[PDB]
Image (cartoon, rainbow over all chains, first blue to last red; front, top):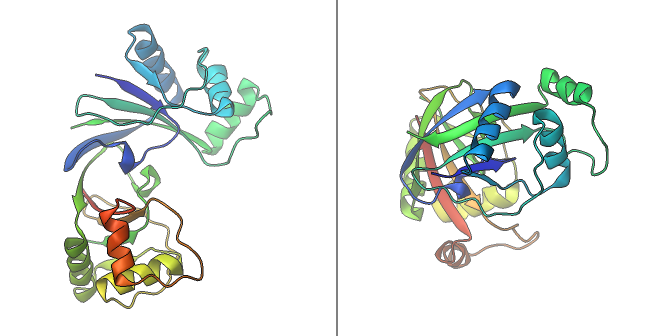
Length: 117
Length: 116
């Protein structure tokens, strides 16, 4: 199925109820590799709507994503790869990979994968 | 066997990963009855931190909740009851029970339950 790239998880992303989903926490490497895999196989749908988050992901993973607004609605065969930022990123501030990995080590960035049980 | 009442579901509410959760949609009556049950058995932890939502729930369900700011973190034996209001409540307006049911008819309020 599809793999949505999102900066949030919401009950609104679930097409139907009841549903049962599994959520794991990812480290950076596994997030970037899964993202790269889904870009290569063409199943990734990018739903990160803001350039700040896009630029962070691109710096972190070496991807070349452009922002894309999509209402995420997941079927039972779909999954999401999620990047969660606590602080609201500055629209303009270019972050070095050292800055991004500080945030990550500080626990200001977390990664998750959500799929159907 | 905690049951949190919240206005949101967020991954930050889960203590440990991996975890597998079931989510169902509730109707008005079932939301309120489940709230009342967990109030009565003392397992409900109210985590609704805005009075506008408090007041709406108290009117809809006949409860006497007050504003309570609580950091929600759920164990495997815990669950949550959720009201999702899709728009901002108007400040200084008292919602009638009819208005709340209108909002619900219109899909502007939804209720869920999340358990493991």
